[PDB]
Image: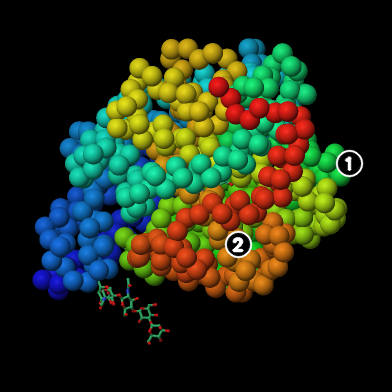
Amino acid sequence: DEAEASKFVEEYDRTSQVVWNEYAGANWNYNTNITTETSKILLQKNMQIAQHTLKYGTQARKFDVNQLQNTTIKRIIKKVQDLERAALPAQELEEYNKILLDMETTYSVATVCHPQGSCLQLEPDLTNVMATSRKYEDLLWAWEGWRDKAGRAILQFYPKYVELINQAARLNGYVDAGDSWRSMYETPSLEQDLERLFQELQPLYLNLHAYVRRALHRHYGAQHINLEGPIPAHLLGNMWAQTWSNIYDLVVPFPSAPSMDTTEAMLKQGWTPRRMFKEADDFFTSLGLLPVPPEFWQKSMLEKPTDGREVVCHASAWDFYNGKDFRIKQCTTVNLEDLVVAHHEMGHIQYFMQYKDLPVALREGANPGFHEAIGDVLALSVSTPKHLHSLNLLSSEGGSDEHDINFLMKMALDKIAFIPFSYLVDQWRWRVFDGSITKENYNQEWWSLRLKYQGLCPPVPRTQGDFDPGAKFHIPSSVPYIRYFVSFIIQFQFHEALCQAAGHTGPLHKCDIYQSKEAGQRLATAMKLGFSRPWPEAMQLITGQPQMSASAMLSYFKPLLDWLRTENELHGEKLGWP
Ligand SMILES: *[C@@H]1O[C@H](CO[C@@H]2O[C@@H](C)[C@@H](O)[C@@H](O)[C@@H]2O)[C@@H](O[C@@H]2O[C@H](CO)[C@@H](O[C@@H]3O[C@H](CO)[C@@H](O)[C@H](O[C@H]4O[C@H](CO)[C@@H](O)[C@H](O)[C@@H]4O)[C@@H]3O)[C@H](O)[C@H]2NC(C)=O)[C@H](O)[C@H]1NC(C)=O
Ligand SMILES: CCCC[C@H](N[C@@H](CCc1ccccc1)C(=O)O)C(=O)N[C@@H](Cc1ccc(O)cc1)C(=O)O
Ligand SMILES: *[C@@H]1O[C@H](CO)[C@@H](O)[C@H](O)[C@H]1NC(C)=O
Ligand SMILES: [Cl-]
Ligand SMILES: [Cl-]
Ligand SMILES: [Zn+2]
């Protein structure tokens, strides 16, 4: 009895490696070369992997998991009983796979065109406009044009997508697809836990919001900024206003302490996409973690092709499920933002290598937020003045109190501003999936949450037919988002624990873990667990306790909260908005 179950998981592991490796290859070939032919092969391989999933999932459901004694085999079999989309009848499976392909292709080939003029892609053209333009109407053209072209074009697919992903979820024992996504955390209290964490970050976010609102009022005019209202969503340096660091120049706390232009420094010094990934590789190995294999450098796509191919530029990391072939696909631009992205993606690669000897069913992060956090932890140290100076991208190490608050502001514009955005995306989607939001009010309810959580308003009133969520990659690509909220909380918990392991003393935000083998050992032991144990065990291995907690992020930013409160008080800001 226990014997049949052990044999079954062995057979599942062997066959899954082969099939998933074949699917990954077809998916890579489409993502890096969008054509009719690669689309057809991918859709065919979708059917092949579904046949495998159905065969083994059907067997798996004949085991009474309650009677199995070994907890690891119990855990694997329970997971294989979830067929995901392979539970759908053949006709609906074919339709679902085609919808997903059509949505991701539509997002990735959308362009915004001037009349009798040039046509702009999202990466790099519109991203660069949002990051560097300081003209209200040019920012508005890019913001509205992207939503008109990408968002509106996804709307025709989204209702049927919702119907089919929910149908598959119900066929696998869940009430809807949002329920199935939340289950990946194995935490019944998840929704309340995340709400409590969000509430703890409100002092910092509200004070940052009010300070940036005041600075935007100074630049864009009192007629365009309401000092007691939400901020127009096209003014924050980013297409989705999800990170705000590109408007640092407008909000510098201490302008008498100027910062080096890091992009021109990287360009002046001949940085390339390959250099950026080599620096990330060096940071990981400095911690005693694993180098990427030679195969990684031969097969990765680290810059946008120039030979005519259309590609999915959105950065991503790829496991080919054979323990040797790992790749990154990124349309890298030479700037500091993409250097952080490179570290993020290399953290995914590191996790793939650390758990490569587990059975494939357990080759995931402890929870999805853990997978997202590894690269970001290292990038916190990369971003310090100490490390950037060592890369020749900043002129000094910043001893002065002024430089210190400036640095904390630059970090807050990315890390704190992202908290409400990352919370709200799946608050919206969870309610779409549970039927609380219908196609009658997709967009209205999106903007209700953008207001409630982020304090943003659309610069142009939305109209029927708008589908602004469709203009954000993870929506048409059906990638869950709450992982990134979890990641941004726990990455500071990890930073704090690794800095302690490294012997750092003094303020947390001055810590740089480069070359700490003690810090690397903590990470490696946790990553090697994969998905074999409840995630609180990996949390306790890294941090010495088992909970998610905002206290580390609050500690990191404590000097900035103090500065922001004083600054906002003396200007008389009214925190929040109606
Ligand atoms: C419940 O079942 C799991 C899984 O068992 C494994 O899968 C089954 C489907 C079946 O094929 C089994 O035959 C198979 O073992 C058990 O978890 C495994 O437990 C073993 C032994 O505890 C682990 O073996 C380890 O494998 C490592 C591979 O890198 C190896 O390095 C380890 O070496 C350690 O010990 C040696 C000798 O002292 C030392 O030199 C090393 O330095 C290191 O300390 C070790 O051989 C598997 O990794 C486990 N697999 C998983 C997925 O966890 C589990 O034990 C069982 N439960 C009970 C209560 O028996
Ligand atoms: C910095 C990384 C940017 C690129 C990253 N790319 C996805 C592809 C995920 C994927 C999964 C399955 C199939 C296809 C893709 C991934 O690697 O997680 C991403 O999207 N980050 C979020 C969220 C985010 C933002 C800023 C950060 O510092 C970290 C995270 C965002 O930019 O909104
Ligand atoms: C792109 O895909 C087509 C169709 O499969 C193929 O013939 C071509 O070789 C591919 N191009 C590259 C550069 O891989
Ligand atoms: Cl939007
Ligand atoms: Cl998730
Ligand atoms: Zn990621």
Residue at the image point whose x is 65% and y is 36% from the top: 207
Residue at 50% x, 68% y is 544
Cα separation, mark 1 vs mark 2, equals 31 Å
Give me the disc on residue 496.
2
For the residue pair 58 and 446, the one nearer the viewer reads as: 446
Q: Total marks drawn?
A: 2
Q: Residue 9 versus residue 516: which sits nearer the camera? A: 516
Amino acid type, callout 2:
Glu
Which element type, helix, strand or loop, lies under badge 2?
helix
In the image: residue 437, left or right of residue 486: left
Say whether residue 93 is visible. no
Q: Position of residue 102 (x, y in %)?
A: 39, 30
Quadrant of the image containing the C terminus = top right
Residue underneath mark 1: 256
Instruction: Estimate the x, y position of residue 558 in percent, counting from the top left.
Output: 67, 50
Secondary structure under the numbered disc 1 in the rendered image = loop
Q: With respect to residue 130, does 441 lie above or below?
A: above
Q: Are marks 1 and 2 in contact (CB under 8 Å)?
A: no
Residue 131, image quadrant: top right
Which residue shows up at 38% across the image and 43% down it? 191
Comparing 396 with 25, the one in front is 396
- Give the residue furthest to the right: 256
Image quadrant where residue 465 sits = top left
